[PDB]
Image (cartoon, rainbow over all chains, first blue to last red; front, side, top):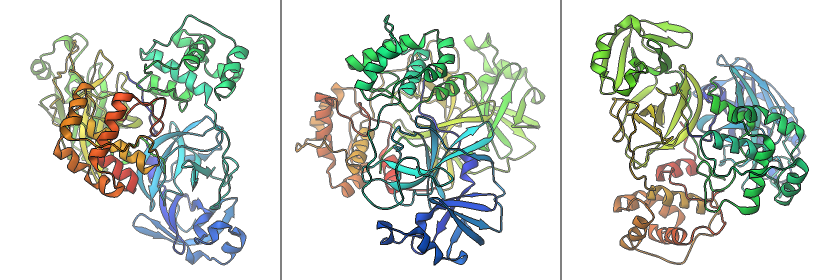
Length: 305
Length: 305
């Protein structure tokens, strides 16, 4: 009973966090096997950060200039390479706490837990979504860079995010664990246009299902609709279009709730067109698009790790 | 930049969770040193739960009837006692992962992270507040009972909550780690009147400060007010009264934000009386009372553990 924004357990990831210092700059890093992953902007000084040539800056640097503190204990850097926008420091020790893990790139709309860190020390954990414009709405102060986002599949930790930039706009940008930015971003302190953000339609849908499951059901209407009809209204309200794929993903919830996806769409249209009239759905006055269909089923069916 | 609802890192607590089975019933338990803490309602069968005499039921039970699975591994129960509404099973092994810890009772308004569990396995983590009527608004399915809530002070884990009841109303009740229920609750499947819940005034205040810190500041007015004046309006909107103590606690934020508590109150009164007019404060259409003054300073100043 009840339904909340819920992060994964952070333990396994906690034991992979390390501090990485280079000259002045210090930030977080991820220690897996004999390799530590971190942002290359560690090697920038303030001036560089306006337009760094990352080729030239690294050439000047050598193993011994990379200080990698694993909590209390130093680690011996024995090699370094740069893969897109990430840095990869090889070290004599393999992390004994290395979990079962993968690196995945995620699609916009998919959620993950962030473990926010300063000086390689865990600070707090929260759930986020990859916004359609490839930004995230997290909580990141100076030093948060290097913090990772991840999912868990029973015992396996898919890392999907590493934080790099706090955009002038106060949202957030970063890379997959192969250094490729999510979105049109680059690692340099400049003005950077992030696009129109739209609302993640399938998630909201999935969120309404959870509500019905939890007895918030005032929003249920008799009406039905069609994809074409609804999308026409979505576009109007900056919602992503809806696809058969989305519907297919919303299938299990339909089967259990006994509410056909397209009637739910009906409910949504009404909300969009009419607002909520001072009503709340699961203690929120607006609609929540940061819950995947999967996210609901896990929470509602009580999956453990 | 940005500001979110953020739980503590769950690792240290993760390694204290164990499954506890007795007859049919199975639920979570907390293994610390050679002691495992769990709800006594484990020893109830369905029928008992309408009106269990906990004295008589335990008398019938003996050590060997308590199955305590530590993930994979069984533990040898070598003694048992009942302390108010908690059960305390002594075992030959002391948990090697036992963290530095305390047990605290918390006051209403104070927040903590819940680690929701099924079969002694971590499921997910979220932040909660002790509502003025001593309920919580979490996410708890059958088996969630035994899950604990806690805070962290650098390296020390104050446990403040263990979950027992999912109330007919769809909110939640439980004990401190000495078994004394928070609130007027008891461990029996009956209708249980939880009181009027009011809104946690100081928290909302503290929350507005974070907003201003994050550049949401449209709600800032020129007006000022007094305690007496404001409280008069609070009572009207079911807000807890405000005390010099609350103000004293809001002092640091005032000093850094340069906004005197009582002007902030001014802003709040206006919001209460006028609503938000379709505006949002930190991506919420209503006001957030589940953030302590401490909670803001940690997040905003970036404290680690």
